[PDB]
Each structure stands twice: as structure tokens, then as C-alpha cells.
Amino acid sequence: MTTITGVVLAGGKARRMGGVDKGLLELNGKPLWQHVADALMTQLSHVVVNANRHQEIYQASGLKVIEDSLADYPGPLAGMLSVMQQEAGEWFLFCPCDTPYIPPDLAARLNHQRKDAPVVWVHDGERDHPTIALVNRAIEPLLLEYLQAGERRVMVFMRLAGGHAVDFSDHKDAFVDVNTPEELARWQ
Ligand SMILES: [Li+]
Image (tube, rainbow, N blue to C red; front, side):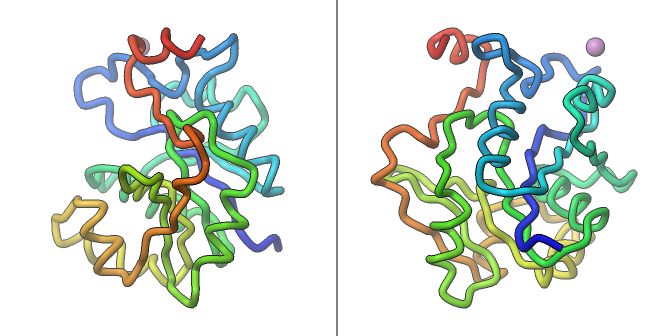
């Protein structure tokens, strides 16, 4: 019913008994994934989270938790596909669980700059963030074919799908990512 579903990508696998659950690390008392979810809810009515560990903890804030298919495909594309297979609706705005400062015009600017492409993603002036991506439904069969072929590379896929980068270089620091607990400590 709404146009774009927001999706927080809070990782798959647990390729050694998980280890650190990055989405649940807390920034000012609030799990990183929830910072992302709250920022997406500012701009979108329907937001879900892809998480494959500690699902009960993710389920605590009342959002739908989507788990990866048993295919166990590699990398962030696997979560994107699992969500498209389990959610209706024509557009998805994906964002990883570690970029807590994403801006309230993320969806609007990506949509304004889509210019007929089926996929666009954020470029922050220094690097591509191909997992912060507005993706049309039509990408679902292409993703499934790519992952079934044994591929994993995210940027390569986004290029094959006919996507382009959208320039968010004017958004100072909105796309900083917190990759480690060590990094997290610096933003408290
Ligand atoms: Li554990």
C-alpha cells in the first residue's frame, strides 16, 4: 500500500557462532539498528528489519523481523533478496544497521534522482554505499539469478542491474558507519 518499504539490514550468517551482533551494539542507550530504523520511520511508514540472530531481541521494538532463506547466500545481497521474497510492494530502501545518522531526505533524494533507473544508491563524496539503495521489485529475479550463480559482489550487481550513484556529498557525515565497537566508542 505505501510506495517504498524501509529495510534495516542487520546482517546474516553467524559464520562462527555469531560473535558480536553489531546491530545490537548501543549508541547512547539505543541499539544501532534502532537508530537506523527510527531514521527510516521519519521518512517512511513501513519499516522492517532483516536479522538472522537474536531475533527475539530485534522483535522487541514492534517491527517485523525477516530472516534469510536457508539457501545461505553470501553477503548483503542475500538479505535484500530474502526481504523482497517476504515483502510485497514495489520499492525498497535498504540501509545497513551501522549508519545511524542517515538523513530525513534519504528516500526523497534517491527517488528524485532515480531518473528511470531501477536501482540507485548513495555516494557520500568519498565512497559508494551500495547497500544504502532504493531498489525496484524488478530487481528480484536478477538478484535471485545472480546469487544462484554463486556470485556475491554488491557493487558489481548494482552495476549489472543498471543502477547509478546519487550524490549526497553535501550531507556532512550523515553516512558515517560504525563498523566496530572501537568505532562506536568514538561517537558516544
Ligand atoms: Li550469543
